[PDB]
Length: 194
Ligand SMILES: COc1ccc(C[C@H](N)C(=O)N[C@H]2[C@@H](O)[C@H](n3cnc4c(N)ncnc43)O[C@@H]2CO)cc1
Image (cartoon, rainbow, N blue to C red; front, side, top):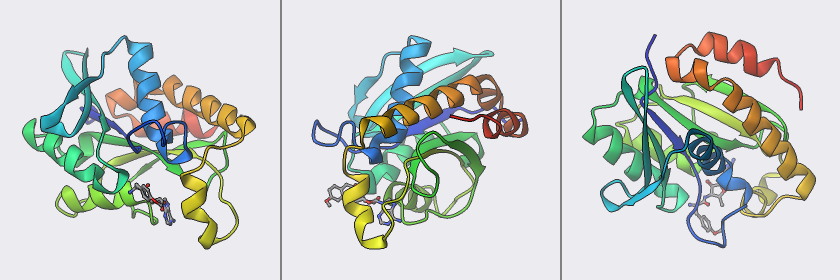
Protein backbone atom coordinates (compact mmCIF):
# COMPACT_ATOMS: atom_id res chain seq x y z
CA UNK A 1 0.00 0.00 0.00
CA UNK A 2 2.42 2.65 1.16
CA UNK A 3 6.01 1.51 0.76
CA UNK A 4 8.35 2.26 3.64
CA UNK A 5 10.94 4.88 2.73
CA UNK A 6 12.69 5.30 6.09
CA UNK A 7 13.59 2.83 8.83
CA UNK A 8 14.90 4.44 12.02
CA UNK A 9 16.74 2.56 14.75
CA UNK A 10 16.75 4.27 18.14
CA UNK A 11 19.69 4.34 20.51
CA UNK A 12 22.26 6.40 22.34
CA UNK A 13 25.67 7.19 20.86
CA UNK A 14 29.10 6.08 22.09
CA UNK A 15 30.68 3.04 23.61
CA UNK A 16 29.02 3.46 27.00
CA UNK A 17 25.58 2.91 25.52
CA UNK A 18 26.43 0.27 22.99
CA UNK A 19 24.89 -3.06 23.83
CA UNK A 20 22.47 -1.41 26.29
CA UNK A 21 18.76 -2.24 26.16
CA UNK A 22 17.76 1.25 25.00
CA UNK A 23 19.81 0.62 21.80
CA UNK A 24 17.67 -2.38 20.66
CA UNK A 25 16.26 -0.39 17.75
CA UNK A 26 19.67 0.79 16.59
CA UNK A 27 20.81 -2.84 16.79
CA UNK A 28 17.93 -3.92 14.52
CA UNK A 29 18.91 -1.31 11.91
CA UNK A 30 22.58 -2.24 12.12
CA UNK A 31 21.66 -5.91 11.58
CA UNK A 32 19.41 -4.93 8.70
CA UNK A 33 22.11 -2.82 7.07
CA UNK A 34 24.60 -5.67 7.38
CA UNK A 35 22.24 -8.23 5.94
CA UNK A 36 21.41 -5.89 3.02
CA UNK A 37 25.05 -4.91 2.38
CA UNK A 38 24.30 -1.27 3.17
CA UNK A 39 26.94 1.15 4.46
CA UNK A 40 25.89 3.53 7.23
CA UNK A 41 27.48 6.95 6.50
CA UNK A 42 28.00 9.58 9.18
CA UNK A 43 26.10 12.62 7.89
CA UNK A 44 25.96 15.72 10.04
CA UNK A 45 23.00 17.17 8.11
CA UNK A 46 20.82 14.34 9.39
CA UNK A 47 22.38 14.14 12.83
CA UNK A 48 23.12 10.42 12.47
CA UNK A 49 24.25 7.48 10.43
CA UNK A 50 22.45 7.17 7.14
CA UNK A 51 22.26 4.32 4.68
CA UNK A 52 20.41 3.88 1.48
CA UNK A 53 19.37 1.03 -0.75
CA UNK A 54 16.92 0.40 -3.51
CA UNK A 55 13.80 -1.72 -3.35
CA UNK A 56 11.24 -2.09 -6.11
CA UNK A 57 12.64 0.99 -7.85
CA UNK A 58 12.47 3.25 -4.79
CA UNK A 59 15.09 4.42 -2.36
CA UNK A 60 14.76 3.14 1.19
CA UNK A 61 16.84 4.89 3.81
CA UNK A 62 18.20 3.57 7.09
CA UNK A 63 18.84 5.96 9.96
CA UNK A 64 20.49 5.57 13.32
CA UNK A 65 20.40 8.98 15.06
CA UNK A 66 23.60 9.96 16.81
CA UNK A 67 21.84 12.46 18.99
CA UNK A 68 21.16 11.35 22.45
CA UNK A 69 17.92 9.36 22.54
CA UNK A 70 15.77 12.30 23.67
CA UNK A 71 16.69 14.31 20.54
CA UNK A 72 16.16 11.50 18.04
CA UNK A 73 13.38 13.55 16.43
CA UNK A 74 15.82 16.13 15.23
CA UNK A 75 17.48 13.47 13.14
CA UNK A 76 14.25 11.89 11.90
CA UNK A 77 12.67 15.26 10.96
CA UNK A 78 15.84 16.41 9.16
CA UNK A 79 15.91 13.37 6.97
CA UNK A 80 12.10 12.90 6.47
CA UNK A 81 11.76 16.64 5.91
CA UNK A 82 14.55 16.83 3.33
CA UNK A 83 13.20 13.90 1.24
CA UNK A 84 9.53 14.68 1.83
CA UNK A 85 8.78 11.38 3.57
CA UNK A 86 5.38 11.20 5.27
CA UNK A 87 4.96 9.50 8.66
CA UNK A 88 3.06 6.63 7.03
CA UNK A 89 6.25 5.70 5.13
CA UNK A 90 8.43 5.67 8.30
CA UNK A 91 9.18 2.64 10.48
CA UNK A 92 10.79 3.22 13.87
CA UNK A 93 12.42 0.32 15.66
CA UNK A 94 12.66 0.62 19.43
CA UNK A 95 13.01 -1.16 22.76
CA UNK A 96 9.72 -2.10 24.41
CA UNK A 97 9.44 -2.56 28.15
CA UNK A 98 6.00 -4.08 27.98
CA UNK A 99 7.14 -7.22 26.14
CA UNK A 100 9.79 -9.70 27.29
CA UNK A 101 13.02 -10.44 25.46
CA UNK A 102 12.24 -12.70 22.49
CA UNK A 103 9.11 -10.91 21.44
CA UNK A 104 8.76 -8.39 18.57
CA UNK A 105 5.57 -6.75 17.39
CA UNK A 106 4.47 -4.14 14.98
CA UNK A 107 2.22 -1.24 15.69
CA UNK A 108 0.93 1.70 13.77
CA UNK A 109 0.58 4.93 15.75
CA UNK A 110 -0.11 5.43 19.44
CA UNK A 111 1.78 7.22 22.19
CA UNK A 112 5.34 7.10 23.40
CA UNK A 113 4.81 5.28 26.68
CA UNK A 114 7.61 7.27 28.34
CA UNK A 115 10.12 6.34 25.63
CA UNK A 116 11.88 9.66 25.09
CA UNK A 117 13.07 8.79 21.60
CA UNK A 118 9.49 8.12 20.49
CA UNK A 119 8.38 11.24 22.37
CA UNK A 120 10.84 13.46 20.49
CA UNK A 121 10.00 11.95 17.12
CA UNK A 122 6.27 12.54 17.68
CA UNK A 123 7.01 16.20 18.55
CA UNK A 124 9.49 16.83 15.71
CA UNK A 125 7.28 15.32 13.07
CA UNK A 126 4.75 18.08 13.92
CA UNK A 127 2.92 16.15 16.58
CA UNK A 128 2.28 13.25 14.33
CA UNK A 129 2.27 9.78 15.75
CA UNK A 130 1.04 7.83 12.69
CA UNK A 131 4.43 6.28 11.86
CA UNK A 132 4.94 2.54 12.26
CA UNK A 133 6.88 0.96 15.10
CA UNK A 134 8.84 -2.19 15.44
CA UNK A 135 8.62 -2.99 19.12
CA UNK A 136 11.45 -5.10 20.40
CA UNK A 137 10.81 -6.61 23.81
CA UNK A 138 13.34 -5.95 26.54
CA UNK A 139 11.30 -6.87 29.62
CA UNK A 140 10.43 -4.62 32.57
CA UNK A 141 12.36 -4.45 35.90
CA UNK A 142 9.15 -4.50 37.99
CA UNK A 143 8.85 -0.94 39.23
CA UNK A 144 8.79 2.54 37.66
CA UNK A 145 11.80 3.65 39.72
CA UNK A 146 14.01 0.90 38.20
CA UNK A 147 13.19 1.72 34.55
CA UNK A 148 15.88 4.35 33.87
CA UNK A 149 18.77 2.17 35.17
CA UNK A 150 17.28 -0.85 33.45
CA UNK A 151 17.03 0.49 29.90
CA UNK A 152 20.54 2.04 30.16
CA UNK A 153 21.97 -1.21 31.46
CA UNK A 154 23.39 -4.19 29.62
CA UNK A 155 21.05 -7.13 29.82
CA UNK A 156 22.10 -10.64 30.87
CA UNK A 157 23.33 -12.67 27.95
CA UNK A 158 20.20 -14.82 27.89
CA UNK A 159 18.09 -11.72 27.35
CA UNK A 160 20.40 -10.45 24.66
CA UNK A 161 20.12 -13.69 22.74
CA UNK A 162 16.39 -13.53 23.01
CA UNK A 163 16.55 -9.99 21.60
CA UNK A 164 18.74 -11.28 18.75
CA UNK A 165 16.10 -13.90 18.08
CA UNK A 166 13.29 -11.32 17.92
CA UNK A 167 15.40 -9.22 15.54
CA UNK A 168 15.69 -12.19 13.25
CA UNK A 169 11.94 -12.76 13.28
CA UNK A 170 11.47 -9.13 12.35
CA UNK A 171 14.00 -9.37 9.48
CA UNK A 172 11.97 -12.35 8.28
CA UNK A 173 9.06 -10.01 7.55
CA UNK A 174 11.16 -7.35 5.89
CA UNK A 175 9.57 -8.04 2.52
CA UNK A 176 6.16 -7.29 3.97
CA UNK A 177 7.36 -4.29 5.93
CA UNK A 178 9.16 -2.73 2.94
CA UNK A 179 6.01 -3.13 0.81
CA UNK A 180 3.86 -1.57 3.59
CA UNK A 181 1.83 -4.76 3.95
CA UNK A 182 1.49 -4.42 7.70
CA UNK A 183 -1.39 -6.85 7.98
CA UNK A 184 0.71 -9.58 6.50
CA UNK A 185 3.87 -8.57 8.41
CA UNK A 186 1.84 -8.65 11.64
CA UNK A 187 0.28 -11.98 10.89
CA UNK A 188 3.64 -13.54 10.21
CA UNK A 189 5.55 -11.82 13.00
CA UNK A 190 3.09 -12.00 15.86
CA UNK A 191 2.71 -15.76 15.27
CA UNK A 192 6.44 -16.44 15.98
CA UNK A 193 7.75 -17.91 19.30
CA UNK A 194 11.28 -17.38 20.71
C1 LIG B 1 20.44 8.67 33.28
O1 LIG B 1 21.28 9.41 32.37
C2 LIG B 1 20.97 9.46 31.04
C3 LIG B 1 21.96 9.32 30.07
C4 LIG B 1 21.61 9.36 28.72
C5 LIG B 1 20.29 9.54 28.35
C6 LIG B 1 19.98 9.59 26.87
C7 LIG B 1 18.50 9.40 26.47
N1 LIG B 1 17.93 10.72 26.40
C8 LIG B 1 17.75 8.31 27.27
O2 LIG B 1 18.55 7.42 27.36
N2 LIG B 1 16.43 8.42 27.81
C9 LIG B 1 15.54 7.73 28.81
C10 LIG B 1 14.11 7.26 28.37
O3 LIG B 1 13.88 7.30 26.96
C11 LIG B 1 14.05 5.80 28.83
N3 LIG B 1 12.70 5.20 28.92
C12 LIG B 1 12.12 4.32 28.06
N4 LIG B 1 10.89 4.01 28.52
C13 LIG B 1 10.67 4.66 29.65
C14 LIG B 1 9.61 4.84 30.65
N5 LIG B 1 8.38 4.22 30.64
N6 LIG B 1 9.86 5.67 31.67
C15 LIG B 1 10.99 6.34 31.81
N7 LIG B 1 12.00 6.24 30.96
C16 LIG B 1 11.89 5.44 29.90
O4 LIG B 1 14.82 5.80 30.03
C17 LIG B 1 16.02 6.48 29.59
C18 LIG B 1 16.94 6.80 30.77
O5 LIG B 1 16.21 7.45 31.82
C19 LIG B 1 19.31 9.67 29.32
C20 LIG B 1 19.66 9.63 30.66
